[PDB]
Amino acid sequence: KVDIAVFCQSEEVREAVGTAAIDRRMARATVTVKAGGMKEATALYGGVTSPNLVVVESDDGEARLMATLETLAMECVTGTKVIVIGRSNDVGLYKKLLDAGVSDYLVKPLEPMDFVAAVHRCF
Image (cartoon, helix red, strand yellow):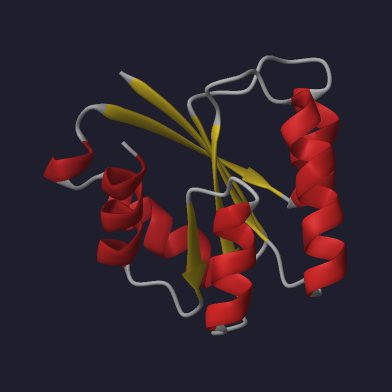
């Protein structure tokens, strides 16, 4: 069973992610939703081993998003996949993230099927 950890602030993300977790296509995964974002994820994975997939909700600028992702990738155990949930719908940003090792980028508003799709895409 795949372990998934979701760090989100928005209720709309939390709801979409929650609806996606109870879906039949998400049977081979255990999703855990935690409050916060990058800071909370980085702080926790500094002491605790990261799960198979870490989903993080971030509204940060390109320069900051890249820097916070470098720091999170340092704490995560090799094999850990990262998905970023953001507000920006930019192809250039999506490309920069995918060249950095992010498995997928999800643009808000998040549909529960977008999250099921993104998880399957990763694996």
